[PDB]
Image (cartoon, rainbow, N blue to C red; front, side, top):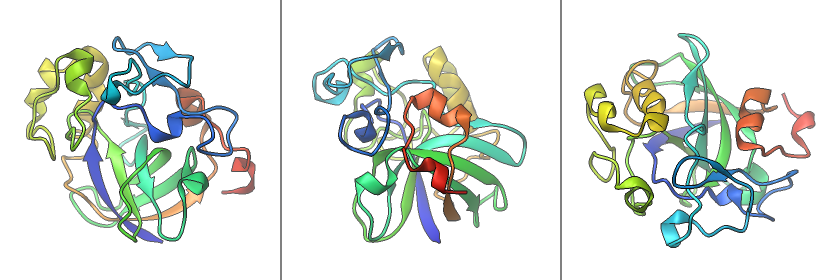
Length: 207
């Protein structure tokens, strides 16, 4: 299947971070203001006055020059949040500066309903979008509301925990802007489920 991509980081608690959102052992971990894991899955989102924010370790990273692991808010045609929360998808970009590169992403949130398939890659400095949870978390992140920063240098002012993911966008991702991709759900690599702590019970039935 094919889909469209975008980028963002609003510091909000991931939608798959609540109980009863997916058939999993436990929901996606959220973190406090200092990027420390919160073990109370009922904690209110930092984007709604609560202490639960997005964890910095839920950032993308390169395995090698051709492959990266990451996280995203997803929305798939004909499916519901229950079908994708904490599921992993193998993506191969079909446009942009890194066309041909591959990336396994775990769904940790839900994107807007557009009728098509789209993944909103979680990338520090990619843009807070509608809800700015980063301001209440640590003062905010620089960059346009949509799209975020424009140059790698801008990552230098980012809180350390968010710098790696910020720079990843310019290094491995070559600052690709909304590249398209083909995808297929695959079994989640341990590196991803261990980071979010969220594993689908049906994960063993996929590639």
